[PDB]
Each structure stands twice: as C-alpha cells, then as structure tokens.
Length: 390
Image (cartoon, rainbow, N blue to C red; front, side, top):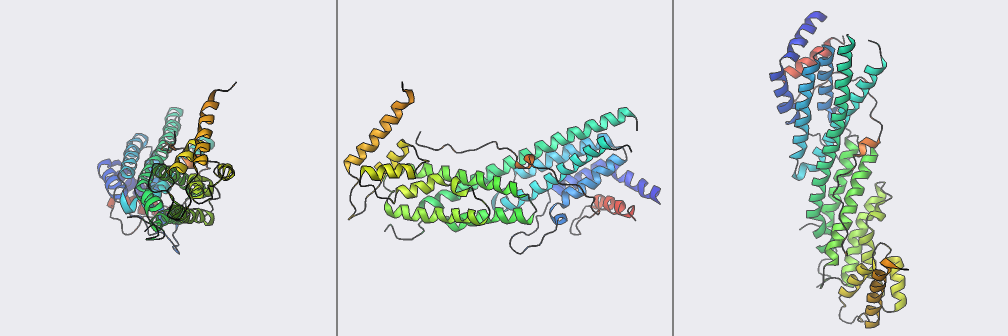
C-alpha cells in the first residue's frame, strides 16, 4: 500500500516538533565521526550519514509539497551545523571539522543538483513552481554561506592550535637536546598528518587539503619568524642548525604529501636558518647572504645579524660588516622617494576552496541510516522511503 506508506510518511513529516528535535539534537549535535587514518577503508555513506539522511527527509518534504516546513526545518539545520562547528575544540578539532566540511559539501552538492533538475525537467501551479525555484535558489545561497562560514571558523581554530604548539616546537624545542648547553616537532607532524589522513579518509577533494595546509604553513612561517626576530640572546650557529632540522622535517613532509609549494610557504624560516649558518666574515659574504635570503628585507637581515650570538672560539661579526648592513638599511629607506621587521600573519577570512570546485555529481543512494543511531521518527521515514523502492 503506497497510499498507506505515503499516509504514514506524511504524518511523520507533519510532526515538526518531534522530527526537528530528533534531527537537531540527535543527528546533528550527537554526531559521531568514524575512525580515520592509515589503512582505514571508509565508505562515503559512513562519512556523510547526516547529510544523506537530511537529503532523504528534505526531498520527501518537497515531494509532499511541504515547502514552507522544509524552509523552517532547514533554518534549524543550518543554525545547528554552524553552532556545532563553533564549539569544536581539542583533540577532536581536525576530524570533526573535516567531517562537517564533507557533510555540508554533500548537502550543498544536493541542492545544486536539485536546482538544476527543477529548472531542466517538466514533471503544479506556476506560482507554486515560482516559489519553489525561489526557495531552492535561496537554499543554495544559504549552504554556500554555511560552507564558507564553517571553513573559516575551523581554519581559525586550527591556526590557534598551531600558535600554541608551533612556536615551542619550531623555535624553542631543541631538536638536539642539550646542544645549546612542551611541544616537539613530532606533535606538529602529527597535526599535519591528522589533516592529511582525515581528508583522505573522508573523501575530501585534494584542492581543499592544499588550501588548508598552505594557509597553515604560511601562518607557521609568520608567527615563528616573528618570535625569532625578537630574540636577543638566542640566535646562534647552534640554533641555526636546530632550526634547519625543525624546518626541514616540515618541508620534507610537504614533498611527500603533494605540497610542491611547501618550501615556498616556509621561506622566512628556511632563509633565517641559512643566515644563522653561513659565513658572515666579508662584505662579499653579506652580498651572497642577501641573494640567498631573498624573502628577508634589509631591516630584517640587519636585526638578525646584529642579534647573532657568537660562540666561544667563534670569530665576532666584524664592525665593518655591521655598518655595511646598517647602511644598506639606510639606503633602502631613502630609496622610497628617488628622483616593519614583522611578517603580518594571514588571519583571513579565507576563500572557501570548495567554492572553486565543481560540485559532487548526485547519483541516487539507498536510504541508509546507521544502526547505532536512536532516532525513531527519522529511521521510520528512511525505512518507509526504502519500502517504496521495492
């Protein structure tokens, strides 16, 4: 009895109090991320289970012409997903963020699919039709905004977590303990490995990984560089070698995970490590140093060189070199009209990389809802939709 299926479907969708509470509190706030990482063979339906359920429910609302109730249901959904991402923190930050980007991307992708199909096919007034094209068009803009918003909320949280770890790991932690006599580089690699693996396991398009990682490495370069350039009894040949090792490990991680641009992201740190290690004896050494250190200004060069701490049995930086560098800075300043030492960290807002990319092609998928969930009305809707496939 399809009329008995449709009758039960219709009454389940009409009861917004129960259905909305189930969707918002159970499905969305109660989300569980599947285990990701190495040798983990996740199917898409394990990743995007909330989106796929919402897609089944939304479409059944539209099938029954509950167009205004879909609108209020979706308003709650959008609200809830954004709030959920806004509360993300701690060890779950990476997996849970990637999880939500995957799901919002799935939802946006469905809405674009729906809009195209509503515009392209003849199946009922043209005033009902007009308000329906209008609603879906508006839903597309709302999901585009949600995606932009959550990408940005999450990326900022990621930056904050790196602020906290990266400075100790890259700048202060000794790669050679005692050599010049708490987070380490391993924690930084773990962070970036988690981003790589979650994205891989949750089927995130590769352009997104590159955008996230490039934004983050550039941020690391800025904040760590800015801490280093302030240090006055710290910069030495030994610290240069240690920094080279810290930096190089990140640079080689980039190489192996496709990030050809990585070396370019880390240039201020790479070139600082160089400055701290190369000979600084002659005027020629300093002109060579400048070409090597193309990403550093004369004022930056001059701060680093002037704050360099010579070891016992190491030759001082000659005064002639110190004044040569000070007079390159004096010249560059004066060149601003011919005839900051800090790098500004990029805090966004950032372009949503999903927006630059074709949406996912919508193939119909079997009405599935995970067994571990406890959503009575939602599960009944899904079970009923699945019955009318037989």
